[PDB]
Image (tube, rainbow, N blue to C red):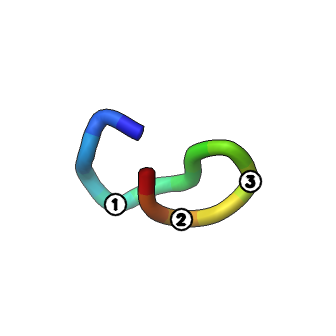
């Protein structure tokens, strides 16, 4: 993702 502490494409991170 855009950094942080959340899900992206089905898991945490990215």
- Asked whether the residues under the numbered discs 1 and 2 touch, taking CB atoms below 8 Å apart as contact, a structural biologist would say yes
User: Where is the N terminus found, in terms of image quarters?
Assistant: top left
Residue shown at 65%/63% (left/top)? 11
Label 2 CA crowd tier, 10 Å (few <14, some 14–19, many 20+): few
Residue on which the image places disc 2: 12
Disc ID at residue 13: none
Other-residue count near label 3 (Cα within 10 Å), few / some / many at <14 / 14–19 / ≥20: few
Is residue 8 shown left or right of residue 10? left
Q: CB under 8 Å between callouts 3 and 2?
A: no
Whole-number angstrom distance, CA of label 3 to CA of label 1: 13 Å
Residue drawn at the location 44% of the way across and 61% of the way down: 13
Residue tagged 3: 10
Residue 4, horizontal then vertical, whole percent: 25, 52
Residue 5 is marked as: 1
Q: Residue at x 30, y 34 (%)?
A: 2
How much space separates mark 1 and mark 2, taking CA atoms? Answer: 7 Å
Q: How many marks?
A: 3
Q: Secondary structure at mark 2?
A: strand
């Amino acid at each position: 993702x855009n950094x942080x502490d959340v899900y992206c494409x089905x898991k945490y991170x990215x």
